[PDB]
Image (cartoon, rainbow, N blue to C red; front, side, top):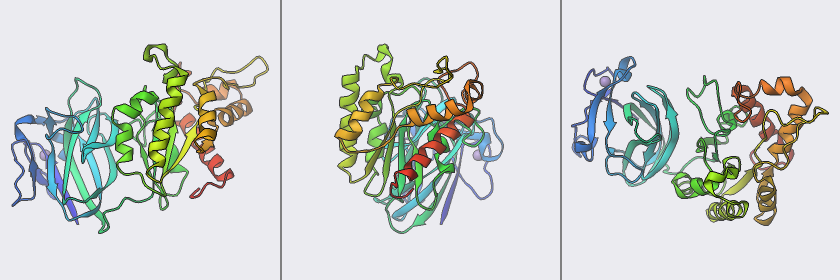
Length: 354
Ligand SMILES: [Mn+2]
């Protein structure tokens, strides 16, 4: 049970159903665009199905400008292949599914339950002003039960989010490396974090809604914010931060799922004269600790655990775990060590599933 669509009008590759921007949704065919007037055929820089694409001229998670495909109810695996891309997200069923994919022909995969017998997807606002294009889709049915598998939903900022290509990016958020440390046969990992995000934004602009749409008992909401929240331009006091964070935790707990809060690690240069790495007062850490106790959530003090690791390897090596000339953003290696520490901590606490 696999449906394959090659979007665009330049070339149609074998094994794929060619879908052009003017192909209006036709129920007798089972697929097509709901509002073709806002779709456009465009060239793409890659090979095969990546040589062409369709561009969504109208977007937004609630936009009717979607590509629809009728499908028997159940759980589906959706592999997305974009066209020429600066930075874009994928939306389906009215909410975000993949956050900020980058690069022409960017690809990623996600699972989604189909309950009304039809999938409605679009590529949407990641970076405003850039082209939101789609080159291909591979839709495969995983189960007749339209229910999601156990999943770890990750919330966060630039030090947590996904960078593309997923397995080749020079930079990475530890949420992107999480899958390399937990059992895939136990958990699915959906890293919904985004660069430069704060608590207020994660809550109000779509990311939380996307997670509340599917999170349920058995799942985990792994949240790490506080870095960007301290920037004055957002005018988000520690008090507001704490309030917003509290609300998100309650909303997620209201779904029966569990919450794991994480204190964000510090800067690569937070070393004292004695060579000890300390960042105990950064990124509103104080409020995160309090919230864990007050709202009874699980807690990974990655701030301290990571500092202990940096202290044990020295300033020079620690510097090699962050982007060059960048003391805030971890590179792939740093992201991998942070993820390692995070899971090692979850196991030490004996948290179910780890
Ligand atoms: Mn094509």
